[PDB]
Structures are given as C-alpha cells and as structure tokens.
C-alpha cells in the first residue's frame, strides 16, 4: 500500500530460472514515482511549527520513517535480488557470456571488485581463473562442439562461427570452447 | 534493519484493539478530522503495531491486552494441548509475535507460554525423518518460519540420497 | 555438508594395495604391495591395471562381533577407522569384481549404519531445557552428523534466543527470550 | 559483511593473520553502493543517517551452535569462556556457540568439525 | 517342530525376513525395507510388496504360498514385529512398545465367469465397477475370561471343561465363559461388494457379484462409482449336506492387495503458478464479457447476447451479510422457455461437463431418505440435493411436467433457503448456497410470452424471484431456416466435432476455465462504485457486483455494467405488458 508491492515482485522471474526468455526492469513506476511524491507529505511537517513540538508526529514519524524503511531494503533487492542468480551464472561464466538480454555501472564495479580475487587467483600476479568449466584433462586443441539448445548467442571466442545452440558445431579450437557448462550445453564434446 | 523477511511490513501490521488508559487525539487515517480529537479511555482502539512498537508500555497511554488466541484459553492449554494441537496457517505470526510482543504487553506471564509449544520439536520431529513421495502430500500446517527449515529438513536428506550412490 | 566433502577427505587416507611420484609413496613394482591413498585405485581398477584388498576391519567376524559389542554404547562404540561409509561405497563398487563376500558386508553396514542413527533420535529425544553444554561424540564415527548438521542448528538459534539466553541474560521473575 | 566490519578492521588494521590485501573490496563496496543508488533515491537522497548507516549488519549472530573437533586435552581442560565448559574430551564434546569460544581457534588448541 | 516339509517355521525361521534383507542392492536404495521407515514418518503401519520378486528370487515359493497365503501374511506380521523391533533400537536405548501393521501386495487380470472349485483358495486379478457397501464397525482377535484367564487365542479372522473348578472337588461344566472385553484387542471391517463387468453379457443375463471383507487400513479408501483391480480369496461361509435340495452354498471373497484405476482426466473429483499467469495475464485482456458469446455453444449458433448473461451467472454475486440477522440471496438464477427443436436439451446436456450438476427432469433425486437398510434395521438418511448443491448449481427442465408433491421445496429454497423437515418428529434444518438454470417446453411459446401472464396455472410467483427470462423460439427466418435445415446434416453426420472450438483465443479449455471460476469465486467481498424498473429488477444488483469478479476487480459502476440492464430488456419485453 505504502510499499507492500514486492508481493507483486514475486512472479517476474518465474520462467526465468534456467529457461529464461528475457527479463524486465518493469513495474517500477509509481512504486517509484510516489515515493518522494509522498516525501512532500513527509516534508509537510518536517520541522514544522504545526504543533510546536509535541507527541503528535512521533506516531506518524514512524509512518515517515517506516515508509522509507521498507522502500530501501526492498530496493536493495531490486538489484540484490537481481545480483544473486546473475552472479551465479556470472560464476558459471565470467564476462565471456554476459546476460542474454546504472546496473551495468554496478556490474562493471563488481567486475572491478572481483579483480582483487583475480589478482591472487592463478598466481600472485593474477588469472581470471577457471572455476566452472574444463574439468577436462586438456586433450588436442582443435575439435568441434555440441550443445543442448543454448540461447543468447554470445560466443565471441576465437572461432569461425559457432551459432551457440545444439549443433553450434564448426572447426572450433580450445581457445573458443572455454565458455559454458550447464546452461544447455554439455551432453557432449 | 532487522532479522529480515520478504514480508518485512507484514511484520508489525497485524492488528489488535487494545484499550486506552487515556483520551484520544486525531488518529488521522480514521474518521479523525475536524470531528473528534478526543474519546474515552477504552475503545475499539485498533493497533497495527509499527507506530507503538517502542512507545512506552510503562507510560500511561495504552493498556494490558491480548488477542484472545494469544490469551490463555488457547495458549495456556495449548501448552497442555501441546500434543497434537494444530496451527495450520491460521495465525502465521505465531512463532514471532511472541518473539516481540508478548513482553510488550507487560503481563509478566506469557513468554514462557510460547516455547513449551516449541519445546515439543525436540520430541516432534522424530516423526520428521524422511521423504517418501510427492512434492504435495500434507504441506499446509506450517508457520512462517518452520516451513523453511522443514524444506531444508527434506533438503539435506534429499541430497544425502545422492551421498549414497549414483542415485 | 555434501556427498563429496567426504570424498574430498576420506580417500586421502592410504592403504597397502597390490599393483616415482613424490610423496611417502615408494615407486611401483610388480608383485609388491604399495601403500597409496585411495584415489589411484580409482585410476587402476577402473583402468584395468590392478586389484586391491581392504583394511582389516573389512571382515564378517570382527564386526560380526561388534554387532553385540556396542550394546554397551549407551554413548558410543568401536570405530574401525571411522570411515566405513565411504570406502565401502567405492570398494564395494569395484572391489567385488574379484573380491569375495561383498554381501554380509553390505548387510552389516546398513545393519549398523541405519541403526546408530536410530539411537540418535533417542538420545536427541533426551535433550531438555536448552541442554546446550551436554553432547556426545564420545566414540563417534565420521560420516553421520552431517545428516543433522543443517537442521537443528539452523533451528536452535531461533530457539536459543530463549534456551541459551538464561546463563548470561535476565529479566523480571518470568523467563526471558 | 560489508556493513560494520569496517569498525572491526579499523580497530587495529589487523595484520597478515586476519585479513588480506579483503581490504581491496572495501573501496569497491561503498563505490558500487553509492553509484547504483545514484539512480535509486536521489531526488531527496538520505537525510540523517546519510553515510554508511548504523542499522545494516549482515551477521553478528554468534550463537550458531558449533561442533567441536576434539583433538586436544581430553580431561576437563577449562579455559576462558563465559558459558559452561565442563566435561571436556578428546573424543566427546559439549556442543557450544561461537562467541564465548572464540579463543581456542585463535589459539588453534581446539578445532572444528 | 515338523522338519520334513510344510515346515511351520521356515519363513520366520530365517527365510523371508532375510530375503527381505536380500532385497538389498547397490545405489543403496534397492529396498522394500525402509519403506516402513518412511511409514514411521507418520506411523501408517503398513507396507507394499510385489508378487514378482519372489519370481525374481526363485520359482519355488510362488506355487507354495498360494496354498496358505493368509497364514503367510500373519507370519509376515510376526516377521515385521520381530524385525523392525530390532530396528527400533540399535543398542539398548529404545523401545516404548511394539505394534502391528498390514502388508499390501502389488500384473495381469482375469474375469468372473470362469472361477470355481478348480481355482479355490487362489489369488486373482479381476475388475468391475463398485456399487455400495457398509461402514466400519468392529472386530478383535483376543481377550480373556474369568473362567480360565487365558488369552482368547483364535486362528481365524469353537466355544470350548469349565476351569472355575479346582477348589477341591467342585466342577462347574457346561461352559460359564463370560468374556471380559476390556482385556481385548481390536481390528476393522467394512464388508464390501461390487458388480461385475459392463461388457461381458450383463444384458441377456443378469450381473453376478461378490461379497468382501476389509481388515485394518483399507476402509475410508473407496466409494462407489469406481473401477478397480484386486486380489482376494475364493472362500465360502456355510457348512453342509428345504434350502439346499442337496447342498447349495453361497459366494464371497476377501480383500488383499487392491489396486484401483484412476482414469486420467476425470479425477479432479476425489484426488500451477504458470497456470495463474495463464489466468491473469489473459484476464488483463478486457475482452471476456462478450468475447465468450461464441463459447458455451462450441457447436451451436444463437443465445449469443444471452451467453453474455452467463458471464455473470456462475461467478455469482455476493452474500454481503450484515451486523443484524440476514443472509440474503447472493445466489442468482435464470429461466428460459420455448418449444422443442431449438436443441435446448443438448444445451443443458453439453453444459453438464461445463462445476457440479445433474440433468434429468420429471418422474426420474427430488427431500430426505428416511428409510431402512439391511443392517440391524437402521433408518439413516441421504439428505436432499441442496446437499449436493452448496456452491454447485443445476440445470433442470420440466417444472410443470413433474409431480406436485416436490414443489413445496421450491419456494422453500429459492426464496429464503427456509428448509426444514418433519418426517420423523424433527426439523433437520440444513441449508445451502444453491442456484439453478431452468428450462421448459411450457404452454404456447412467444404467442404467450410477449402478452400477459398465464403460463403456470398455480402461481405468478415464478416471474418474481428470477430475472433473466429470454425466449426460446423456432422463429421462421427463411434466410436462416435453410441454414438450420442444413445446420442439422453436419450434426447428423460423420462424428468429427470433438474439439473444433479448441483453436479459439480463450473460449475453451474446460479444465482451466472451471479452475478460473473456482479461484475467482473466492477472491474477496467485491462491490460496485458510487453509482418496469421496480424493486425486482434492481434486487440485477447481483450482476452489478458480478462485473467486479468478471473483470476480477473489486469495484465497478452502475451504467458501464448496465450491460446487464440492456440484456434484461430482452426479458422485460416478455412481461412488461
Ligand atoms: N442449430 C442446430 N444445430 C444442431 N442440431 C439442431 C439444431 N437445431 C435443432 N437441432 C436438432 O434438435 C434435436 C434436439 O431437440 P431437443 O433439444 O431434444 O428439443 P427439447 O430440448 O425440447 O427436447 C437434435 O437432435 C438436433 O439434431
């Protein structure tokens, strides 16, 4: 009412678990466009002589204060809730394959924040370190690929053209094939 | 700013009608206006908690009071009837009302009433051991909190299932 | 807590086997036993390279004596290397390719595995009154306690608000959570 | 635990033993928390607890009942701790929480399971 | 101990218990074993098995147990109470007390017209369709008596020496055995019954049947109107040789290992959020009110703007009770009327599948069933059909062509729900949230309807309590008369039209629609907005509140939702004048 609205948030990610068509930043307008619309209500008596310092604004100070209090930490979620399983697939891959579809500034900040990890990782000097692919013992470097209906088509890795779904298969070397595991790919090598 | 929940304003929004030690003044969202800024001590005086969450029970503003499920007639014999008593989904804020409120009332009797319900878990979830079958058999007699670890209760065993073998 | 936290661990132990990498391991010689950690017999038996025989507790006599020994265990029992819920997993997978008596083996282990948990509710059906500083490992095994590790302890804090709170936190005459 | 770990890490700037060059994430913590918020609530952005505020803390609950790897003095080897610690053991244990026994594992006398 | 053959111990000696411990393979899940352990999740006190593991184990026991099965199963009771009670405790710290369980067996069926002495005391799979049966009364196995104070050890589920004697000389023969049932044990029963198949000449013959015996856990499981596969026993009840001109006897069987049929798509009767997206993200479209005017007739033309008035009907109005007494008529009804040939029969027949209803009219439920049964001559009732309609509603023809007896219960339900009985000296005052669709072939069609009021010769009351009465005709319209002359050869021929309406945007999917409704009619307490037209035109307000739940909204206004008014103008022209 005054922000009980995330009960509505709950459905946006429903298909979007491991069969994601696409995401929406949506539904956010009046849950946003009221919030400091109603600051004007919050400021109506903010340091006002309307009652000259008595009880009568403390019970609604709580309205003034709770109103924020819920807005923030839900609005933590709107990225944090969105940072979580995106970090997870962004663990499943680095920025080898970002999202199939100021969050980019926070992602770039998170990518710069992850640098610390990368510095010690692999060596003192640092390696974006393989954590999520090639438990392969490495074999000969130039043999092709197979998938299980991947989608997004971000394979930018050193190949002729792969067309990243099942039968994304061309003469693709090891440098190419270093992308993904469990987003519709690894029935096969 | 709490031990959070997704419903963090379905936290202190349950309503009770505890009486007034005092007269009234302009509840705002009510029929208050240029109509009434004063009533009696004691009235159907509705209390969605968040405004009175730290508003000095000790101070003469409002009264010792209970919602009658939280009164002894349920609770004090729900600790006697702590055997196959049901909670359903009926008043879900019932592990957690008393984690806040029941002291705030200031009748210095009711906190102990609670746990001896939840003391039963040390001899309840002997039955809770395992998962036979489907995802929906009897999954509707929960609180807002026990369900989570109950799912988790399944969960470690569900993947303890794969600890065994290829299964 | 996992299926393979143990297999991170338990296969690190070593035993003399039948068939140089640096380590206390010696080089490998035909006809000549060699103590190895158990994550090579993977890479031999499944590689169709060599066999292996078990430790000594692996028998149907010493632990067909334990079947009654632990009835002392109002607390706990004899623990032959503590890890017979993991090795037997992999041993009995592939060892019985030529090993005899893989059955009473398979019997007893479930006939001791499920059981010592069957007590475990019971001893846990003795916990009363926030009895946090009483517990039991006294001759515990290795591969059991994970199956309760996530459940009650991620319960008891939301209890121990009221259970463990007493011996440093106080209120008026009634009890405090 | 970006929240108030600054206070602990500002107590002594704990040396090689405690954190590591963990300190690099601190600079990125506020940066990503500020930049992002630059388009969250900025028309009338925070008013009294306007800095790294007081109320957000991730994990100060110290009572997460911990199992103890008994590898130590078996007998009732009693140590600095506020709750009961009677009846010590090299195999057994009396299960406990983290706060009061934050000592043995800084010592690494005692151990964890 | 008779250690030659028929050995009395073998099973519990080692064998079956240990085979069960041989039911033990890798994955560490191959078990018929911890089955009970997941029964001890609740204490169901039973277990399931096959008859094709013993075949996977041997070929020796399957022809053996068939001789003495009901002996083997209490041998298995013994096996269990010896086995799991070992498992109640690892080491000596657990047992409150033992208990007892049941076992469930289960492959390939049989029939009933082939089974006699040849296959007696043999376990069989057959199938029929259930009819009715008893409740659950009582049974026990053992107790004891003052006279000897020994447990009432019985084999089967005669009557004895006195033994209140040895007080010196005194005897006391001729059986002073006074049972002390507070010492006793206890079991269940149902005594069931079923009829044989509908395909194996039940027509030129008559259907034969079987009598049955339930034991512990298997009652409260099965209600008639069902089709089952079962195992039993071929036994009888009497003893022998002016009944029985020589020796005639009677048939029955037992219960063992029922396995029922759950045939597919009937059973949202007895036993997702993506579908909620389907509900609502379709509901967002403001195209449902008049969109479905081509829906409830998925094979018919007409009634179009009257299907417009079904859109409010099932969704109901609101039982907006008050601080004072009333529970007024939230429910709403309809009337239709006209001659045959308009397919108004099939309109109700096809509507049966489209929430809960029945479609019969006249001389062939009704009132109560205050009659007797066979069982110690009881008198117990069946209720009415406000019973069977308390959120369910009905579509029923031939008010006029039906007995005049069961017509005080029409005003005693449509007006007030003022229901009561006095058969035996009492008023069972049951109630229900019922409503009805009505049809008729009443007197003289539109020549009667438009003009005044003479349809039924007993009451003018039938125009008062209902509102939407739109005429059924076989109007002559020559441009469409030939169409309806050839709207009846496609119907007459070729058996094609099963799901021709399935492609429609959102005027199909029976299951999703019924669920659409049966969520919708449980949203809140919707209402409307600030916003001969007499008191029962108005008391339409139910339809006003309806469009809140038709748009699935809370609120709505008067005259956007006077769509209903403009549709009612169809009816009012009948009886304006
Ligand atoms: N438009 C139509 N489409 C299909 N069948 C029709 C149509 N109009 C009439 N019929 C015929 O009407 C017959 C049914 O009449 P019925 O509904 O039984 O009359 P009543 O309802 O008075 O008993 C059906 O056999 C059907 O062939």
Image: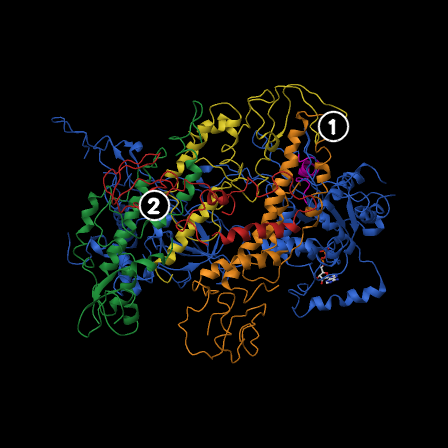
Chain colours: A orange, B yellow, C green, D red, E blue
- Segment tinted magenta in the rendering: E401-417
Where on the picture, by quarter, is residue D73?
top left
Q: Secondary structure at mark 2?
A: helix
Disc 2 vs disc 1: which is toward the camera? 2
Pointer 2 residue: D105
Whole-percent x, y for residue C125 in the image: 33, 39
E505 over B110 or under it: above or below: below
Whole-percent x, y for residue A157 in the image: 54, 73
Image point 73% across, 68% down: which residue? E489
Given residues E518 and C163, the one toward you in this image is: C163
Subunit of label 2: D
Left or right, residue E10 beside residue A121: left
Pointer 1 residue: A50
Quadrant the C terminus of chain E occupies: top right
Subunit of label 1: A
**Does the magenta-highlighted stretch encompass residue E411?**
yes
């Amino acid at each position: 009412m005054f922000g009980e609205k995330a009960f509505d948030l709950l459905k946006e990610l429903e298909r979007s678990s491991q069969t994601i068509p696409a995401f929406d930043d949506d539904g956010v307008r009046q849950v946003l466009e009221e919030i400091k619309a109603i600051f004007e209500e919050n400021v109506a008596q903010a340091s006002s002589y309307n009652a000259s310092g008595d009880r009568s604004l403390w019970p609604l100070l709580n309205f003034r204060h709770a109103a924020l209090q819920r807005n923030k930490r839900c609005l933590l979620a709107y990225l944090y809730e969105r940072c979580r399983r995106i970090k997870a697939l962004r663990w499943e891959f680095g920025p080898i394959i970002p999202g199939d579809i100021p969050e980019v500034t926070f992602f770039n900040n998170y990518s710069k924040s992850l640098a610390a990890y990368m510095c010690s990782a692999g060596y003192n000097q640092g390696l974006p370190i393989d954590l999520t692919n090639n438990l392969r013992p490495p074999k000969s470097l130039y043999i092709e690929v197979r998938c299980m209906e991947d989608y997004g088509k971000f394979e930018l890795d050193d190949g002729e053209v792969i067309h990243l779904k099942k039968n994304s298969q061309h003469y693709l070397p090891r440098a190419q094939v270093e992308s993904l595991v469990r987003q519709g790919i690894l029935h096969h090598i | 700013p709490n031990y959070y929940s997704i419903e963090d304003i379905f936290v202190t929004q349950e309503k009770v009608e505890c009486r007034v030690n005092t007269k009234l003044q302009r509840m705002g969202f009510l029929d208050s206006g240029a109509e009434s800024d004063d009533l009696e001590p004691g009235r159907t005086v509705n209390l969605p908690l968040w405004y009175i969450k730290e508003l000095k029970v000790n101070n003469a503003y409002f009264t010792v009071a209970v919602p009658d499920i939280y009164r002894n007639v349920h609770k004090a014999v729900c600790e006697a009837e702590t055997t196959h008593i049901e909670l359903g989904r009926l008043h879900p804020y019932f592990y957690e009302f008393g984690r806040y409120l029941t002291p705030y009332d200031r009748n210095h009797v009711i906190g102990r009433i609670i746990f001896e319900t939840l003391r039963q878990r040390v001899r309840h979830l002997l039955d809770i051991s395992k998962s036979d079958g489907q995802a929906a058999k009897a999954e509707h007699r929960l609180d807002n909190i026990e369900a989570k670890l109950h799912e988790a209760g399944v969960r470690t065993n569900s993947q303890y299932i794969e600890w065994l073998q290829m299964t | 807590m996992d299926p393979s936290i143990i297999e991170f661990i338990g296969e690190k132990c070593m035993i003399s086997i039948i068939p140089l990498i640096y380590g206390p391991v010696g080089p490998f010689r035909a006809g000549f036993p060699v103590f190895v950690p158990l994550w090579m017999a993977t890479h031999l038996r499944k590689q169709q390279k060599c066999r292996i025989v078990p430790p000594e507790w692996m028998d149907m006599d010493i632990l067909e004596e334990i079947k009654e020994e632990e009835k002392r265990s109002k607390f706990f029992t004899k623990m032959p290397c503590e890890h017979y819920m993991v090795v037997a997993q992999l041993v009995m997978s592939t060892a019985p390719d030529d090993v005899p008596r893989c059955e009473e083996l398979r019997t007893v282990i479930k006939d001791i595995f499920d059981i010592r948990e069957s007590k475990l509710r019971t001893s846990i059906d003795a916990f009363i009154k926030g009895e946090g500083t009483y517990a039991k490992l006294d001759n515990l095994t290795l591969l059991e306690i994970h199956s309760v590790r996530p459940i009650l302890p991620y319960s008891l804090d939301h209890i121990a608000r009221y259970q463990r709170t007493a011996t440093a936190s106080q209120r008026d005459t009634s009890m405090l959570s | 635990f970006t929240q108030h770990i600054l206070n602990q890490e500002e107590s002594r700037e704990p040396d090689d033993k405690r954190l590591s060059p963990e300190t690099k994430f601190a600079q990125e913590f506020a940066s990503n928390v500020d930049e992002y918020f630059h388009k969250v609530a900025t028309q009338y952005m925070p008013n009294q607890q306007r800095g790294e505020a007081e109320q957000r803390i991730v994990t100060p609950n110290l009572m997460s009942h911990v199992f103890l790897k008994a590898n130590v003095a078996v007998p009732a080897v009693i140590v600095g701790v506020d709750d009961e610690e009677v009846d010590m053991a090299a195999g057994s244990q009396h299960i406990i929480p983290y706060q009061l026994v934050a000592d043995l594992i800084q010592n690494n006398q005692a151990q964890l399971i | 101990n008779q250690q030659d053959a028929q050995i009395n111990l073998q099973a519990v000696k080692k064998k079956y218990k240990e085979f069960i411990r041989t039911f033990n393979e890798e994955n560490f899940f191959y078990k018929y074993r911890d089955t009970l352990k997941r029964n001890y999740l609740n204490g169901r006190y039973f277990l399931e098995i096959e008859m094709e593991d013993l075949v996977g184990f041997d070929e020796t026991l399957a022809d053996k147990l068939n001789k003495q099965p009901t002996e083997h199963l209490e041998i298995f009771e013994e096996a269990a109470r010896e086995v799991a009670d070992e498992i109640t405790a690892p080491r000596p710290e657990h047992e409150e007390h033992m208990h007892d369980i049941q076992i469930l067996l289960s492959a390939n069926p049989t029939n009933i017209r082939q089974l006699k002495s040849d296959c007696v005391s043999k376990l069989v799979k057959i199938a029929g369709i259930i009819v009715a049966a008893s409740g659950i009364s009582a049974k026990a196995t053992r107790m004891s008596i003052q006279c000897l104070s020994c447990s009432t050890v019985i084999p089967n589920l005669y009557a004895l020496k006195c033994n209140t004697e040895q007080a010196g000389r005194p005897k006391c023969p001729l059986d002073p055995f006074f049972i002390m049932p507070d010492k006793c044990k206890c079991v269940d029963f149902q005594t069931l019954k079923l009829q044989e198949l509908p395909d194996f000449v039940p027509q030129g013959e008559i259907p034969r049947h079987l009598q049955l015996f339930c034991d512990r856990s298997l009652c409260e499981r099965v209600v008639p109107g069902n089709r089952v596969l079962i195992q039993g026993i071929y036994s009888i009840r009497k003893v022998g040789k002016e009944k029985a001109v020589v020796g005639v006897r009677a048939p029955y069987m037992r219960v063992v290992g029922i396995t029922v049929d759950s045939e597919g798509a009937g059973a949202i009767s007895r036993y997702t959020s993506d579908e909620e997206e389907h509900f609502r993200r379709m509901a967002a479209s403001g195209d449902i009110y008049e969109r479905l005017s081509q829906s409830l007739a998925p094979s018919i033309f007409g009634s179009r703007d009257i299907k417009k008035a079904i859109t409010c009907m099932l969704f109901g109005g609101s039982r907006k009770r008050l601080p004072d007494g009333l529970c007024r008529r939230g429910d709403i009804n309809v009337l239709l009327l006209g001659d045959p040939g308009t397919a108004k029969s099939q309109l109700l027949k096809f509507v049966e599948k489209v929430p809960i209803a029945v479609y019969t009219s006249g001389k062939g439920s009704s009132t109560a069933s205050v009659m007797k049964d066979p069982q110690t001559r009881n008198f117990v009732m069946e209720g009415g059909a406000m019973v069977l309609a308390d959120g369910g509603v009905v579509c029923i023809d031939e008010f006029d062509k039906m007995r005049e007896d069961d017509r005080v219960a029409i005003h005693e339900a449509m007006e007030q729900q003022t229901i009561s009985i006095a058969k035996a000296g009492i008023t069972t005052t049951l109630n229900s949230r019922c409503s009805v669709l009505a049809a008729a072939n009443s007197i003289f069609g539109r020549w009667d309807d438009t003009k005044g009021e003479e349809n039924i010769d007993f009451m003018p009351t039938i125009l008062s309590r209902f509102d939407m009465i739109f005429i059924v005709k076989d109007i002559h319209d020559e441009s469409r008369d030939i169409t309806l002359a050839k709207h009846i050869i496609n119907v007459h021929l070729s058996s094609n039209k099963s799901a021709p309406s399935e492609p429609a945007e959102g005027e199909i999917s029976l299951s999703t629609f019924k669920k659409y409704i049966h969520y919708c009619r449980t949203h809140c307490g919707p209402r409307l907005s600030e916003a001969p037209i007499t008191v029962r035109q108005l008391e339409v307000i139910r339809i006003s509140e309806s469009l809140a739940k038709i748009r699935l909204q809370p609120f709505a206004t008067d005259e956007h939702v006077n769509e209903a008014l403009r549709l009612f103008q169809v009816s009012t022209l009948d009886a304006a004048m």
